[PDB]
Length: 88
Ligand SMILES: *[C@@H]1O[C@H](CO)[C@@H](O)[C@H](O)[C@H]1NC(C)=O
Ligand SMILES: *[C@@H]1O[C@H](CO)[C@@H](O)[C@H](O)[C@H]1NC(C)=O
Image 1: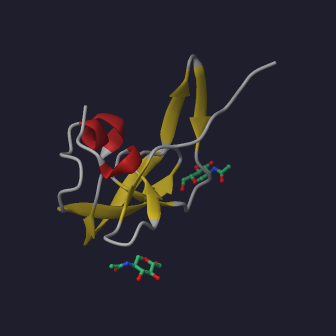
Image 2: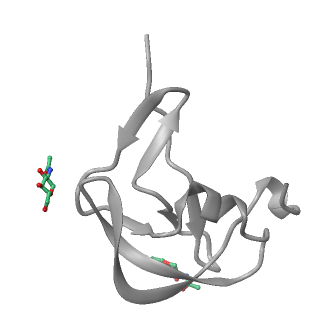
């Protein structure tokens, strides 16, 4: 019974995933990533609103107590759908 499910990610030009929020809904189950996990602080809708295959500078951060805390560095990043095809 229940629960949990994987976090969404963006990748760099080569496909290395970095998650994009530190919390998730799983239907009504909430997950929180461990304090310290790499993440981009852009959010699930931040991810959805990104044009498939185009590059964004995504602000890097580290997770703490469920929020991606930015670290003022930035890194070049990507939303890739199945078969690279176009968003939404
Ligand atoms: C993305 O990251 C991984 C490890 O952090 C690395 O081996 C790879 O070359 C990276 N891709 C680019 C284009 O920077
Ligand atoms: C993670 O870090 C925060 C604040 O730095 C702390 O208050 C919190 O209890 C920590 N949680 C765990 C399980 O490490």
